[PDB]
Length: 25
Image (tube, rainbow, N blue to C red; front, side, top):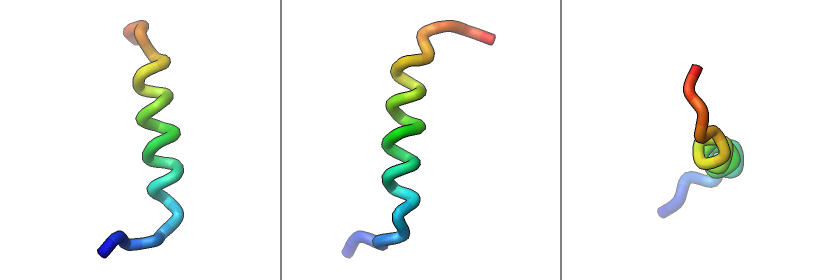
């Protein structure tokens, strides 16, 4: 059972941001 919270979309977007971020801070 998947917990449909909606936040999973943000998770995957942030995961995408993590892939886009190929530079350090």
